[PDB]
Amino acid sequence: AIEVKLANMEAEINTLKSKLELTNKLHAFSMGKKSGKKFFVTNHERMPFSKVKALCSELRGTVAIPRNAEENKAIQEVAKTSAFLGITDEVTEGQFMYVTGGRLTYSNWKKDEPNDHGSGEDCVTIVDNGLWNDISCQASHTAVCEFPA
Amino acid sequence: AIEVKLANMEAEINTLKSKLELTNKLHAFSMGKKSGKKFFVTNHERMPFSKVKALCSELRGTVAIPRNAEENKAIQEVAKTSAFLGITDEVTEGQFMYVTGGRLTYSNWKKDEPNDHGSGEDCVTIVDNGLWNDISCQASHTAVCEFPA
Amino acid sequence: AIEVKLANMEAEINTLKSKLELTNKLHAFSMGKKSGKKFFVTNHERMPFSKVKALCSELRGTVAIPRNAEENKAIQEVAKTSAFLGITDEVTEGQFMYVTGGRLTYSNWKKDEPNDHGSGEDCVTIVDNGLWNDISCQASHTAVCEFPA
Ligand SMILES: [Ca+2]
Ligand SMILES: [Ca+2]
Ligand SMILES: [Ca+2]
Ligand SMILES: [Ca+2]
Ligand SMILES: [Ca+2]
Ligand SMILES: [Ca+2]
Ligand SMILES: [Ca+2]
Ligand SMILES: [Ca+2]
Ligand SMILES: [Ca+2]
Ligand SMILES: [Cl-]
Ligand SMILES: [Cl-]
Ligand SMILES: [Cl-]
Image (cartoon, rainbow over all chains, first blue to last red; front, side, top):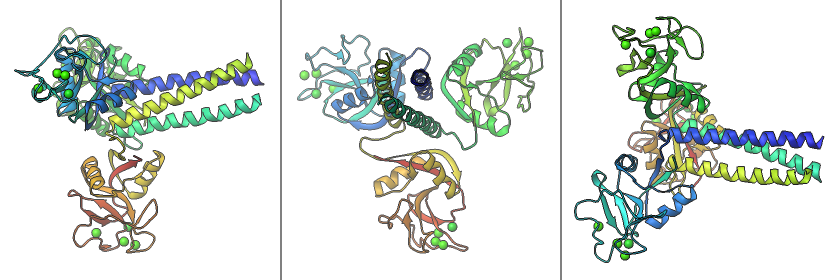
């Protein structure tokens, strides 16, 4: 009977949706996602900023953005090496903004940074001791993505 | 036409279900699951026992339970820090039972434990060297869930 | 109704397929998959060659095979200990072949290897120098699976 088969199909699809959600929750938990907190993931690959943005966007995340000290430390831990943050002053020199919009608030700049060095630096990397340095968007640093809480 | 479309979609569905099962298999393997052994996993978050139970049930798992010295060792290495076990003596003082049911088979109490210290301690935690200490269920410890072999 | 519901379910199936693809991409990323590069994964379990092949087969992968020094180094780093490679001379003693078919191209044999020692050695393990040694297929070494670039 077509209708009974259609109803079973709806149930099969709803069951699959729920199982996929469960799979997504288990993976986030295994990646260290804390309850009600956003999480960070890296493949430890170094690449220019444009590639990190593309990669994270493709995974439905964004380049990691430290909004506070705890998150900064979490990102530093995940990365292990220098890594790009989702913060740049490409739109207007001197005004750092998050890739997702809004003016930069919390910061952890190394002493004497940002300094738009040489020909100019519009991207930001979390470096030694978790401090920040503005650097060329064309330089290759570790790709760290963040996913919603 | 319609009956054919429906049959073709039932086939796509079966294939998708098998593909998701694969994703689950590969994820567990990547997280260290050994052939024929229970899969133990943590996000390294410390919280009260009530929360651990809720979290593990939310992922369709259960709070980690060491049924023997080998599983106890496995849990010890996953947790790294003090972690709640799925065991309590909430029914009868001194009678430790698994949250999933039954009397405790294996145990690894630390010297002078269990002591039901102070106002009482009805939960259990695996601590240094993998030894056990009873503790208040309200205290916050690492959340470690288990999934079937 | 019938046809509308059937059309909706096709949309649901395609949406679910896209979501599962996303989940697989994100899991590959967390597993360390580098852009356009093949990747290796291990659960750190040690088992006989027969079991490694069966396990990787279940996961839709293959026993890790280094096609060059780069891949050889990657497998060495994932395994951490001796691990089996998808290379054997089981068919014809002395002529090592990939389990995936074809004659062994790249090789990194330790001096004096392969020597089919004692009772016989038909499988190959990448040792703690990246160098290779032929060994009994019955011996238990780390299972490292390889997935496509
Ligand atoms: Ca500029
Ligand atoms: Ca600038
Ligand atoms: Ca700078
Ligand atoms: Ca009590
Ligand atoms: Ca007690
Ligand atoms: Ca105690
Ligand atoms: Ca032989
Ligand atoms: Ca041989
Ligand atoms: Ca040998
Ligand atoms: Cl720049
Ligand atoms: Cl208690
Ligand atoms: Cl052999």
